[PDB]
Amino acid sequence: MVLYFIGLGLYDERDITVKGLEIAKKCDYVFAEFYTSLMAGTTLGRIQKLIGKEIRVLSREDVEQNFENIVLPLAKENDVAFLTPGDPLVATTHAELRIRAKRAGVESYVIHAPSIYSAVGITGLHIYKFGKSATVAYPEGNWFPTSYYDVIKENAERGLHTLLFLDIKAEKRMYMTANEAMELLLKVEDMKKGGVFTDDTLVVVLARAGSLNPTIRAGYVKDLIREDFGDPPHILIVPGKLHIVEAEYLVEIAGAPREILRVNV
Amino acid sequence: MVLYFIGLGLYDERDITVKGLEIAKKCDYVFAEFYTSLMAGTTLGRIQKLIGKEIRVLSREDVEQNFENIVLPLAKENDVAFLTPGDPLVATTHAELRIRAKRAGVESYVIHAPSIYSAVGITGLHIYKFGKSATVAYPEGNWFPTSYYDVIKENAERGLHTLLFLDIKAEKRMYMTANEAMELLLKVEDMKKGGVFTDDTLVVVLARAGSLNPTIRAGYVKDLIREDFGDPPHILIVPGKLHIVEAEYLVEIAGAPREILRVNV
Ligand SMILES: Nc1ncnc2c1ncn2[C@@H]1O[C@H](CSCC[C@H](N)C(=O)O)[C@@H](O)[C@H]1O
Ligand SMILES: [Cl-]
């Protein structure tokens, strides 16, 4: 009669919360999805080993179209767990699943876990200064989406930071790198000439957040566009005007050039 | 030899990640602060029991003025952890403490935990639509803070949601309620008259996020301003223009007036 939405956290199998683990262990059935994002620092096997349960992976179609047929039925007479990377409900489509549960007469509860949305605080940038978020999508065919560029412009215009999620082909396990994202943005700039993203733009790269050894780098596009930030996942941030304390953290912790202390503050 | 910043999560001791727990259990010394936020579902004792170490609580002054005199000295010869509610680097000035660690020759690592900043996803409002965040501070003496009002205005004109952290006086054991936050906003509205926050404004209240049964309520200020949302901590949200699916969730899950379903495109 109960369905638990449980977050797996940022990077590996230990990023789930103690509450999440214990509840998942007591569940009769455990499902999971790995299409909204991936858990780069672990494997399905390692997660299964930790939970001590068989985990049935569901595709986007399984969830978006058949959640009420695959998961909810068992949730009616048993304790069921639905695992997702990060924090449950951050992915725009997950919240709606609770409405499906309600209509099927199933109670649902949410067990949170660290999300990249909050983990970016490790960049030294003030969380309250982050504006609207956006996703950089790979162009393809005659389709060249560029809305994420406008999001940066509107945020930066108001002195706000822009968190950019990078595209991911979950099934194919292909990760968009910060480098590729910078190239795309430069390409978009060259097309809109809005003076939003150029070689002189200051950016921050956060790679493998959640890991004990994440890569935190800050610098101008011209110097970072071809830098190796390590293995994915990568997240790109275009900060707005910086508070001196943010700048000093980027210099001292993220190896940013001293120049930011006078050019971006 | 090392200093760890470890988040404890939203509500109780079990909101700490497995990673944070395993690492804390092995540290030689464990310090913590409980003034940046309120964990309403546990106690120092329960945390100490779970971690299996005595936890020395530090005050805001101990941290802000003597972190390098109380904590860092031990980190040079031992494994030390600094515990905080939620995520250690979200809506706090703890990031700067890493700079102090560096300058003191102490390597530091960060272990994330669930943060209110992303837990708001449980309100059903899309995370990416949240703009700049702000804090509703208690008026004191002749000083009456009003900046949070402008943040709402700026976000709303852009169709963005506004997350409002509510003030806290840990030592005086005072936790601002959503009701008090609303009262203050109505006053600032009278003062500035920007049509930003009135009795007809739709708002969302999230209380005790992290618990299995947090209070999630949506409605017009005139109707919620006197409603009892239970014990603290509380968070207040002023939505911007809603997507139909967001309104859907607010109605079905947070009991919002069914009229908000009729979104004005
Ligand atoms: N479980 C919870 N429910 C509602 N609000 C919460 C909350 N935990 C924190 N807050 C809000 O955040 C304020 C502290 S701000 C510090 C937040 C912390 N670093 C985090 O990551 O959550 C509180 O006064 C309250 O308004
Ligand atoms: Cl500011």
Image (spheres, coloured by chain):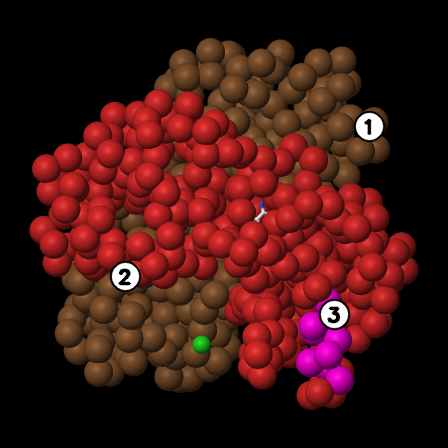
Chain colours: A brown, B red
Residue A191 against residue B223 in the figure, above or below: below
Tags 2 and 1 on a common chain: no
Of pointers 3 and 2, the one earlier in the residue sequence: 2
Which x, y percent locates residue A217?
A: 23, 59
Chain holding disc 1: A
Res. B172 visible in picture: yes
Q: Label 1's element?
A: loop
User: Which residue does the numbered mark 2 point to in the structure image?
Assistant: B65
Predominant SS of the magenta segment: helix
Q: Label 3's element?
A: helix
Which x, y percent locates residue B128?
A: 56, 58
Magenta stretch: includes residue B257 = no
Q: Is A101 left or right of B73, judged from the image as shown?
A: right
User: Which residue does the numbered mark 3 point to in the structure image?
Assistant: B183
Q: Which mark is on residue A104?
A: 1
What's the magenta region? Answer: B182-190
Chain holding disc 3: B
- Mark 3, ligand 1, within 8 Å: the answer is no
Q: Is A252 left or right of B211, judged from the image as shown?
A: left
Amino acid found under the numbered disc labelled 3: Glu
Observer-nearest of B180 and A207: B180
* Residue drawn 54% across the image and 33% down it: B42
Amino acid found under the numbered disc labelled 1: Ala
Chain holding disc 2: B
Cα separation between marks 3 and 2 = 34 Å
Res. B18 visible in picture: no
Which x, y percent locates residue A230?
A: 21, 46
Residue neighbourhood size for the residue with mark 2, other residues' Cα within 10 Å, grouped as few (<14), some (14–19), many (≥20): few
Give the number of the mark in front: 2 or 1: 2
